[PDB]
Length: 162
Ligand SMILES: [Cl-]
Ligand SMILES: [Cl-]
Image (cartoon, rainbow, N blue to C red; front, side, top):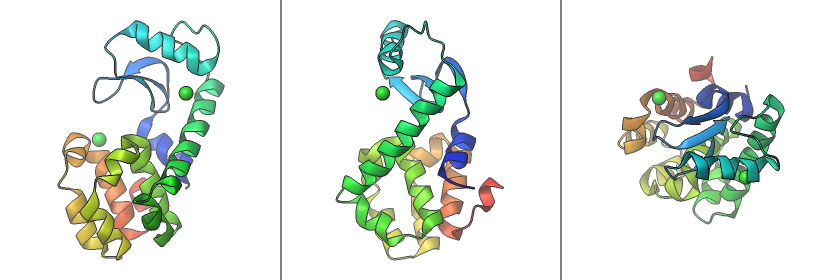
């Protein structure tokens, strides 16, 4: 298992614009297009992202190319972030994938705000960190995906995904 297969289980793949769990226009593998209510503002972003006139539909390959950019950006954002970097550096390979996942989903700003949990991870207090992470809108809103990520943090194995 690796970050790509993990995120592909959590986000799915859709080749036509769809609305995410929060109601926003997305396409491919969890690629957020816009938070604007307009489907047109969504198709415009999409065409800008792909470099062609897509009419709201893209190929598997285009979907995978967006995914490659997004995971790459997620990693680079963590490494540029003063709050996140020290956390990531301290973690093993499995847990690192868990933090990338949260970033991909909620952005660097959002994750960076989980101050207390971050401190617990850095300290390797797994059980306490898992308990704290669960007290969040995140866990309340997408409980099944949150449990998987949380279990990856507590355990350090990919069990939740197998
Ligand atoms: Cl883009
Ligand atoms: Cl969920």
